[PDB]
Image 1: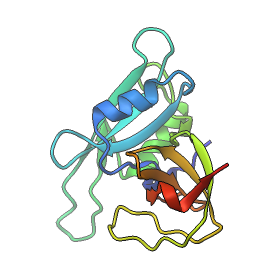
Image 2: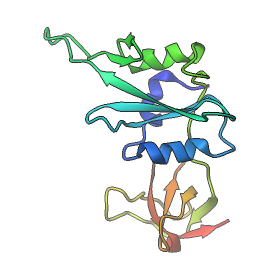
Image 3: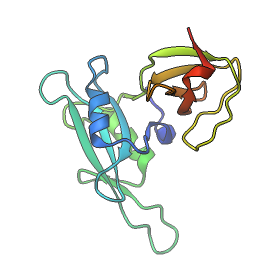
Image 4: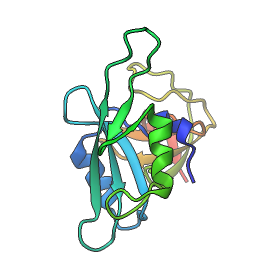
Length: 170
């Protein structure tokens, strides 16, 4: 289960092919899990999908944006395969029931959690990549980026850097 209009949630700005291939290759990830990210073709997006456990395990799809209709009445269409779709919701829904190479879109990728912390001090942040949080607030750590700063996710799903020392591991 996934909602093809929350697609903006399964999009990971900044993640490379290789990153996604590594995240989706992990062995506890199930068939039909997928995410979206910047394609390495300038300007485009790609879909990365865990499609089998033996043989080729992860597939990558280029999604090509059309030009919008001059009219000014457009919304550029999106293309994957030879299959065109007036947008992304529709594209993503089509592949719930049809196969990509060996599988079908089933659940959106979430990074798994390696710590539950509760924050011991309000953090307001200094960089746009930081995650602000209140003293007492519960957060899921997903990655220990360096010694003093870790990647965290909050109840609403937003991610960024918190200071290790402003949080208390459970």
